[PDB]
Length: 90
Image (cartoon, rainbow, N blue to C red; front, side, top):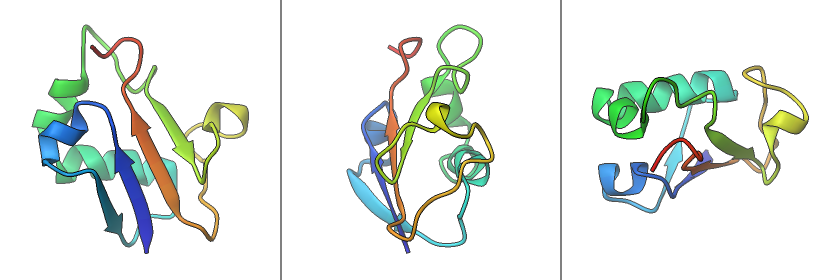
């Protein structure tokens, strides 16, 4: 199982702070999963202006993906993802 943390508008969107997931082993599939599971309400609540994911900040197993991989980023055995609100959001 993989643990995911919410800090951005996603928190008040799902009414939670932490939850587990299964089936996701990559960031690319993870992000797309959030928009689907949470629906458009999440994508819109996060989309401020034009783009959001382009500024979105996600930490994989405690580390920025920008300093490694973009959408092909993978998670470690630890399985831990963090979602924070981008400078464009809010």
